[PDB]
Image: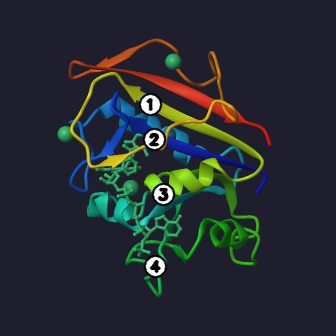
Amino acid sequence: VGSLNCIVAVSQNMGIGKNGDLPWPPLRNEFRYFQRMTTTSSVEGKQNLVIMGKKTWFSIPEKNRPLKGRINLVLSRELKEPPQGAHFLSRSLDDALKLTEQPELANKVDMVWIVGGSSVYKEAMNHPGHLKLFVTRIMQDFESDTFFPEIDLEKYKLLPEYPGVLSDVQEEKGIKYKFEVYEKND
Ligand SMILES: NC(=O)C1=CN([C@@H]2O[C@H](COP(=O)(O)OP(=O)(O)OC[C@H]3O[C@@H](n4cnc5c(N)ncnc54)[C@H](OP(=O)(O)O)[C@@H]3O)[C@@H](O)[C@H]2O)C=CC1
Ligand SMILES: CCc1nc(N)nc(N)c1C#CCc1cc(OC)cc(-c2cccc3cnccc23)c1
Ligand SMILES: [Cl-]
Ligand SMILES: [Mg+2]
Ligand SMILES: [Mg+2]
């Protein structure tokens, strides 16, 4: 794999989770953005792969697992096989990316999207090579128990705009947020 993508929504206080769910009320269009970004494949016949930690998997509403239109991979050092509904299981990020080269996924995967949680993002953000981080900045503090590792601007640059991504502040349910894209190249 030549490029990885992370996607996350983060409160002002760096929160991403609270009690096995999101810290904020449901933001419909922000979710549709997550869906659009993670689902859209550039290649006919291929789907994107989503990689996530175990608690993130269980934080997805069951009726919606696995995430439709995408290959779902779960990370765990304890499970012996994928959670019911998940397509693949890996013991590490490294192992997950190597799987895409193996005969079963050979030519089935387009883009790879890391979708949390904290430790998965931390490792992915430090992985060699090209990486884009799609970060929704929720412009409010929310009570959280799970947090996003701060972005090291020695490695990442905030892109001023980006094709396919709205630049202006968004608002849903009185909650203001902005979509950001960060990028590192090596
Ligand atoms: N706002 C947002 O964009 C996002 C928010 N969330 C929220 O975050 C919370 C869940 O995230 P979090 O608590 O951090 O947990 P995770 O989803 O990261 O799950 C943690 C578990 O997953 C496995 N795991 C995690 N990292 C790795 C790794 N690098 N390599 C191998 N296995 C790994 C381990 O499982 P094991 O113990 O089996 O080894 C670990 O115990 C929820 O509240 C969820 O709603 C989640 C995603 C995005
Ligand atoms: C959508 C919140 C969000 N935004 C951004 N920018 N990045 C993210 N990683 C996430 C997230 C997340 C976890 C999560 C929680 C959840 O429901 C509580 C649902 C999803 C989810 C993700 C993808 C497709 C889904 C389809 N149907 C229902 C849910 C889907 C995904
Ligand atoms: Cl923006
Ligand atoms: Mg689904
Ligand atoms: Mg809260």
Q: Do the residues labelled 1 and 2 touch (CB within 8 Å)?
A: yes
How many angstroms separate mark 3 from mark 4 (CA)?
Answer: 19 Å
Q: Mark 3 points at which residue?
A: 119
Q: What's the residue at 21%, 54% (across, down)?
A: 19
Mark 1 or mark 2: whose residue is earlier in sequence: 2
Spot occupied by residue 6 in the image (x, y as percentages of width and height):
56, 45
Q: Name the residue under label 2.
A: 8
Q: What's the residue at 50%, 38% (across, down)?
A: 150
CB of mark 2 near ligand 1 (< 8 Å): yes
Amino acid type at mark 4: Pro
Spot occupied by residue 109 in the image (x, y as percentages of width and height):
68, 60
Spot occupied by residue 156 in the image (x, y as percentages of width and height):
67, 33
Q: Are marks 2 and 4 in contact (CB under 8 Å)?
A: no
Mark 3 or mark 4: whose residue is earlier in sequence: 4
Tag 2 secondary structure? strand
How many angstroms separate mark 3 from mark 1 (CA)?
Answer: 18 Å
Amino acid type at mark 3: Ser
CB of mark 3 near ligand 1 (< 8 Å): yes
Mark number for residue 66? Answer: none
Spot occupied by residue 73 in the image (x, y as percentages of width and height):
52, 67
Mark 3 or mark 1: whose residue is earlier in sequence: 3
Mark 2 or mark 4: whose residue is earlier in sequence: 2
Q: Is residue 65 left or right of residue 152?
A: left
Q: Mark 4 points at which residue?
A: 82
Q: In this view, does 28 lie to the left or right of 48?
A: left
